[PDB]
Amino acid sequence: VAGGGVALIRVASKLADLRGQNEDQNVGIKVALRAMEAPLRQIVLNCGEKPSVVANTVKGGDGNYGYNAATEEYGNMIDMGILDPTKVTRSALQYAASVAGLMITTECMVTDLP
Amino acid sequence: AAKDVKFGNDARVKMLRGVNVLADAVKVTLGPKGRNVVLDKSFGAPTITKDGVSVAREIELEDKFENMGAQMVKEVASKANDAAGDGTTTATVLAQAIITEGLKAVAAGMNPMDLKRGIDKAVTAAVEELKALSVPCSDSKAIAQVGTISANSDETVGKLIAEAMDKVGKEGVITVEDGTGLQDELDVVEGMQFDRGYLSPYFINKPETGAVELESPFILLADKKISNIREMLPVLEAVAKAGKPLLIIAEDVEGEALATLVVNTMRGIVKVAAVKAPGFGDRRKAMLQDIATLTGGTVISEEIGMELEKATLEDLGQAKRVVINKDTTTIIDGVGEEAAIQGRVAQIRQQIEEATSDYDREKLQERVAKLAGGVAVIKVGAATEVEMKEKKARVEDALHATRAAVEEGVVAGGGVALIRVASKLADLRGQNEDQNVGIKVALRAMEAPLRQIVLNCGEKPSVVANTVKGGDGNYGYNAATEEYGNMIDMGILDPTKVTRSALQYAASVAGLMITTECMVTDLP
Amino acid sequence: AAKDVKFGNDARVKMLRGVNVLADAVKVTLGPKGRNVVLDKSFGAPTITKDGVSVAREIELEDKFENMGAQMVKEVASKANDAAGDGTTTATVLAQAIITEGLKAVAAGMNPMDLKRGIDKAVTAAVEELKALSVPCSDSKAIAQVGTISANSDETVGKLIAEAMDKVGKEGVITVEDGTGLQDELDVVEGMQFDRGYLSPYFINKPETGAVELESPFILLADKKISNIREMLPVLEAVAKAGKPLLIIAEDVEGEALATLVVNTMRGIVKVAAVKAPGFGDRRKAMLQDIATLTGGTVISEEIGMELEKATLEDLGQAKRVVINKDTTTIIDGVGEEAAIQGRVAQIRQQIEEATSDYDREKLQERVAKLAGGVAVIKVGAATEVEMKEKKARVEDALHATRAAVEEGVVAGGGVALIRVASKLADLRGQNEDQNVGIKVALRAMEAPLRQIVLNCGEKPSVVANTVKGGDGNYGYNAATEEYGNMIDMGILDPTKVTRSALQYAASVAGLMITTECMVTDLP
Amino acid sequence: AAKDVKFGNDARVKMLRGVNVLADAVKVTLGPKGRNVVLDKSFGAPTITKDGVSVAREIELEDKFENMGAQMVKEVASKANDAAGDGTTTATVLAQAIITEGLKAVAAGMNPMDLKRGIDKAVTAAVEELKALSVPCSDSKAIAQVGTISANSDETVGKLIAEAMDKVGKEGVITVEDGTGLQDELDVVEGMQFDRGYLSPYFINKPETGAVELESPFILLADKKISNIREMLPVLEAVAKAGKPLLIIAEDVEGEALATLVVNTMRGIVKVAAVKAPGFGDRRKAMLQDIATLTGGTVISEEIGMELEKATLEDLGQAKRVVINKDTTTIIDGVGEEAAIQGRVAQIRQQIEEATSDYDREKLQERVAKLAGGVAVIKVGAATEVEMKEKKARVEDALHATRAAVEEGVVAGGGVALIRVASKLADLRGQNEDQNVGIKVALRAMEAPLRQIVLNCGEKPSVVANTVKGGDGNYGYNAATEEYGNMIDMGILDPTKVTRSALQYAASVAGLMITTECMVTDLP
């Protein structure tokens, strides 16, 4: 799928309608979606860019329309040669979400005294 | 002397941090199930109130910067209350909203000057989209209804207001006084009202309304500036006698004279208030005369060798009661001869028969109006002095809401009017992505009032907001009975003029702060 | 008493550190998208302004040294505003630029006295290279156009100014007052104006413009110095009567007398202002007379046994209104007999027919000019007192910019005039590498104004600057519409006199500070 | 374990603060009026040196972060000395320069990744602009001249080098040993040299040059990795006998075996050094043979059931002397039969007559070269052992500078070569303003070396720099005689290869640090 973190940002803009059983769960959704923009927004940021402009632009298009941050030029990511094995993007996300979940649901920590 | 200066981001969080204290303290009194705020008072027992206006008056932080922030939204938010007689708490919770997301967007790197224009546009639109939602209100059948709703449903009050507006017109002048017992009284008396406020607070003696008030006072009409009390002594100490308070109307009062008076008002040595003559130029000189005629007595203009010394007690004017606001002076019942005044209007009309212009005509038939219209004076009556002072309070408030609906109509209350107007502009866009955010920020903010009212009621803000955004028109949510429906029909409304004001004003300051880069203040 | 002394490098960073606070606080206003600066005010609601002049007036740091630094660029930067009625913020952001790189170069080991000369050269050149870029402005078709652009495009104002200059000449005297209603009035009255300022601030009562102002005052003309009030009592308390303010014109007022008066002006016990007689020598004595004739009344010169005691009330002068600036006294409408004044000019002309010199001739036909030219008085009119006081403000400002264009022409605004002048001197060199740096520093600095205006607009300073440096003439960048082109044609200009001023002044102080090795101040 | 992490700006000043200690301590040695640096030594009398290399070896700060910074420029700066035999101090003062203004620009808000590219460009250019300024050096008339200048003008040394290069070619192999008395000796012996360094310092025993050195040692040629000493015991203790040091050449030595040996070298129980066989693949296997033939003895490859146990003493190789550097092994005088070796070259040439490729051909005629070229061995002679050990030092250094000129030519010394190259690129620009700064920073930096040499001489850096930037070519400033002119002619030059190196390397680390955002290190 499209690299440079766009694959995620696209998938996110496609689920704006998604909802859950109650307002909390909705936030739960909105939090995860908001988060999926991090990778891209950081790549951009590392490049001394304007994260918001570039993110909104990518969220505007459809498909693998991304932003080759290497040449500051938008277009199709796969054609430009910027991609990531779907398996890694899926993994990174599922895993991140796993630990994120666990910690958000932690109430107690036990450890050794210094 | 030495100052402290903060810049950009640093200086902004300080302001926000400050306004948050203001907004959060004042917004818990918002909405039917609003909570109490306990205002400790110097010596005595605290004050428990739910009046946002009172809570804001006291708020004032310690950090010089945070204060400015809070002090800034207060200056404007009160501007809304002074225009429609209500909607301060509203304008405040609004400004907090705009400001919060706005400064959030700035940190997000976006441009300030654009977020601003984007906001002012989203508002400019909401205001027109609001005039359309506005249900008219012209037949005295409606006046009597709005005045009623604006007084916990006392069909008496509504009627009273109406009977009055009927005697002097919607543009007339209506005054409220204490009754002489059970049963209400109403009638018009030779009076007048111009747009001039007190030349300084302090004179105020009815902080309940924030205005001055004088019984059977004297009116000093002098065409000239006054900065030296030495010209008052002759005809000022002669007023300490008779104990009759004195109203000075002159082109203006400055420094020495003014300060000297602002002093004596607290030191009880004579209670006098003075304000600027109305208008300017030759017209001011003429209007000064109108007043004199209407209140009996004469004007003291240098133009004819008259000095404030060669002025006895009869040269002075006199009426049965005056009332000064932050920007309004109104003379009630003038000693003026009901025959001489009729003669002055004679001239003014034979001066229109020589109106070699259009502007000149209006301004003249605008003067006969004041001088010939008179003033309606409602005297609230009740069973006991308490009930009465209370009712006179409700009437005074209903008389305010009424005039705001008669001017611009009314709209759904409970904060729905705004939330509707907002859902109607989701398509709205601007010149660039920043300006678009500017728009989306303002729209998002317009939900604050409702979402808070709901929140104060231990509800689910989101559910209730979406539901209201679903319907159309004045389909709202009477938070008092947890039941949706038409707001106007349920009796939950706000004079369009106050909702428009609260918004325009909140947006004003929000904009200014989002576009501030530097703050300068004193060192602690 | 005990002092603190800092030296060389140590003492310099302190100044810079100080001027930076001044410059940064004031420059965020620069250009179309300028931001607001919130100035906290003792008691009341803060003041939100974008006026660089107001922001600077308040800045004053705590560190005794840093202050001097900031206080130093303010003394000069204001000198520019007093000369062309504008360009203070500019001169400031300029001095920051020069100073920053300059002290940077000093640390770099280079010589200070050379960096200076290198800078003064780069400037001396920029000023001539600026007179050339200057588009003339002499036909009243242009006056009426500049006056217009200098007032948000009110073609009325421009016209008004022109009609005035047409009556008294480009060198005439134009005064602005309040109107007597709708419609403007203009006409010339027997008046005069000399180059003398108030003998002390405080007298000021219109801090809005920083000047004095007296209505139908009295003018005391005494040829002699005055340091003892004991000579005023007879003819000063006699002025407390009639309440008519008093203007004292004497060779000079010192200590006891002066202080004693500066006191009473705040204590309201009589509002009087006094200034030094014009010129010096025998001419001063003669001009004093001119004034007397023009304002009716007589001069009190010791030369003939006259004492300030044997002076009644008619011996005194009198006019309908006076106005004192930091360096200008102007008498408007003199009681003087329109027949006696005509007789004085008789002498002065029969005294030129005996002009055994050239200098002597000019100075005389220079007096008839003042005494015979009179003064033009514009009375701004508007619909309401508010609109009017506002318009009168715009006219007063346009009347200033106009006179600065009539004298030296106008050039492209938005800071391009400077950036152009800079790109034209890239070849310029001096006596040694240091002086060359001196040049390059000043040139680099002349881009600050534009680069800031652009920056305030969330732009890319570099792109925009290079582009402007690419073209030629008044090819600029209207930052208000993000579109390049001819600045004069787009209506974005600045009187050459102000741009020249801002630059010359900024360079002055920048030079002085770069050449400072020691600072002495009080111990905290 | 627990670590300390610093970020961005915070972490950068730490590095800089660190590298500054390094640079300032090392640069005060620069050029002829270079000062001394006193290096305290554990027990004994301090060491007074002007050798920047030695001063840097010792520098190592306490603050974990600052250290890294200093430790980072050292890693690279030494890389320059290892490539051209000189130019470390240079590369350091350079890196300080780039880094200082660079991080200064970052704080100025500019982009790091751009400053970098701008710098690398400015360099990429300076390198080509340097190859052009480079005066060739091919005729043995020049070699003998450069070798001379690179030895305080001992025309003997220069000649000696030349006579040698003449026998083995510019690409030959030249060795320097102690002489057998007065008079120098030179001759070629059956030897060889490959690009493999010691498998670990410590083995080093001539820290004066930082290399190993063995007299009439044994050479162990085994095609295989070795990590277990248990395979050495049989043929290692048999080497403790005869006391003849041992050189192990195997595919590689790891852990247990390696460590075990690095131990014994300090514990005197046998002095052996080992290095990796040359090349890789089948060629490595073949080259291993070449060595064996050349040094008499055989290879022990598992491929044919041979074990490091069934290996006597004659199976082992032997030569008259070896020398290992950080990346170079060189065998001098092999026991190998001058008749058998001639037979091996027989095969290698009849293997080229079957060269079904081009690559394959070069790599083969590259082997005969090593195996048939032999090694030139210069034996410095002098009057006394002292004079001699000293001269042998000079020759060893001149032999290095010479080879760096023979490869890439020579350019003006005293830091002018760089300052010239810099003034030639003033026009150079990049894709954006940041990159431009990147360029300007690198150029400004290239003046450091000269400006320091001058400074060490109590001169006026600026004057002298501008003067040199005025002229063209190798017009420099012999700081030794305060007289300008042609540097090459005056005898002040540097092998182009070292100047190019110092620059490329300095720029490398400078870049990396300017682009660092995070540092992680151990907690104190």
Image (cartoon, coloured by chain):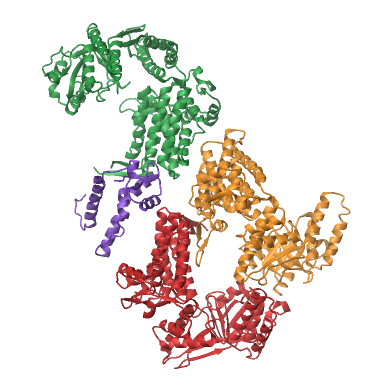
Chain colours: A purple, B red, C orange, D green
Residue in the image at 21% along x and 58% along y: A107
Quadrant of the image occupied by residue B486: bottom left
Residue in the image at 35% along x and 15% along y: D171
User: Left or right of B164: which side holds D113?
Assistant: left
Q: Nearer the viewer, residue B509 or C308?
A: B509
Residue in the image at 34% along x and 51% along y: A62
Question: At which x and y percent is residue B431?
Answer: 47, 56
User: Left or right of D339: which side holds B116?
Assistant: right
Q: Nearer the viewer, residue C221 or C501?
A: C501
Can residue C8 be seen from the camera position used here? no
Quadrant of the image occupied by residue B108: bottom left
Question: At which x and y percent is residue C408?
Answer: 69, 50
User: Left or right of C340: which side holds C432?
Assistant: left
Can residue B273 be seen from the camera position used here? yes
Q: Nearer the viewer, residue A70 or C311?
A: A70
Quadrant of the image occupied by residue D293: top left
User: Left or right of C381: which side holds B79?
Assistant: left
